[PDB]
Length: 121
Image (cartoon, rainbow, N blue to C red; front, side, top):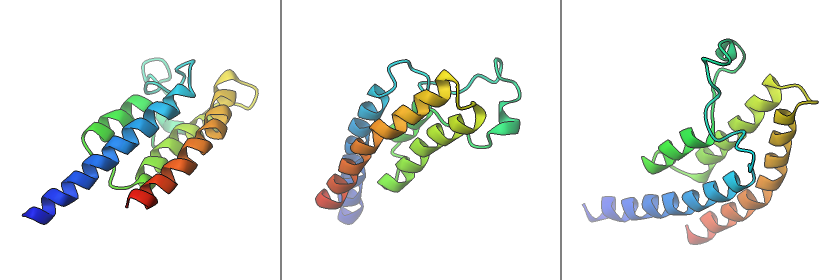
């Protein structure tokens, strides 16, 4: 149908907007602390602590499969990266501090992305 195609064009445009957002969020992690999943070979107990692991490469695979229906689902995944880190790592660690900074700096980007998604529909 012609509707399904129109739908697919907007999903594709959302994917386009979210791709740009993801690149901007990832630029706020220059140390690449959140770039890849936490290694289960190197942290074998991780899943006893964190039930829903997330990282920027995993978000990217979902993104490119157009697996994000809306910005809310995307934000959920971003928030997991942050919140998982702030639970597993103590406050005085480079990792915890890196998450706080990504959260703070990320807020500006997500703020504008919400306006852009509402605005363009």
